[PDB]
Image: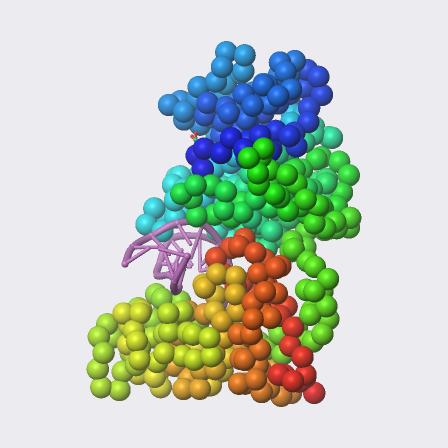
Length: 394
DNA sequence: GTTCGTGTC
DNA sequence: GACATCGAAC
Ligand SMILES: NCCSC[C@H]1O[C@@H](n2cnc3c(N)ncnc32)[C@H](O)[C@@H]1O
């Protein structure tokens, strides 16, 4: 995934279209395997262009035009009919935590250039917006990117943008990059029309085959899910979990790190600051320490008020599943979701926990969100259906 | 307040 | 595969 597998390249080329003599671009091209593959497949009567930032990487055939620039700050003379490629992925931030390292002034420039830039954001998001803006009307884009933009908040504006700028086809590939931890999708964007079509794929020796899954003709940027009749059925059967509960996150690690009550060793009256490694399906391991942090249990409420109260805990970083337990002791947590019943909500804690851990709930989330992200996110959690057995809003 | 991507066994 | 980041980001 500084290299794309040949069958991914070929799959993408099979989705790509350009008029005769039309302008074809590969951003972050290096040696330009997408331009090479498109030319092998469709011939030579096109204008082939490759943008690369690193002169050690730029190595195009003499029939293509190579440009040494930052694709994201680059201002071409003319727009393009087709843009295809594999964007660089990663968060721009401090080298101690994040992979992309640019001067603050450059990231300032990126944030000014991109209307979709939200939160920490990502290089692959910036690349997608850049490319759509360099398309002529009716132009086509074919990119391979992580799947995380289908569901995540950072990419809400990117999704709204794509829905507003034309028509979108999404093909799920999954973990198709050897030795890279990512679930991938192929986007086919065309700068005209509207709506969204979602596709699954089939992988053979002959390569990838698209399987039409679902169509959203009036898509506006809504989260993208693999919906079935079964998932729809379960979703109407109860109240959304978010209507019953206030959903809060744990206090972060540095909040605890600097609190005068928190120690780095166990001792009299001291209790471990819990993490996801303490949370199990239906129970909490209060004994083990995984954070390296101890504090008096009674002092936990100074970090979050709700730490003083027995409440429901749901997992965030165990993949796309629902792992829940009742925290009857009310301990300090460094991780996970913390759910507080809304005014007039009658709950049955053990019966609700039991339902959230159930195999029915596991399939449900795995069907909708697959392996897009290594998390149960707030957006997935709040839409979980809860029938009257487990919680009732009077 | 809380988000996001591998990191390490 | 297991089993989850954890803190700089806003
Ligand atoms: N398309 C192949 C994978 S992405 C890796 C390539 O993207 C290039 N790259 C990363 N950021 C870039 C940018 N902002 N503009 C142009 N090329 C970039 C790298 O130099 C590298 O050759």
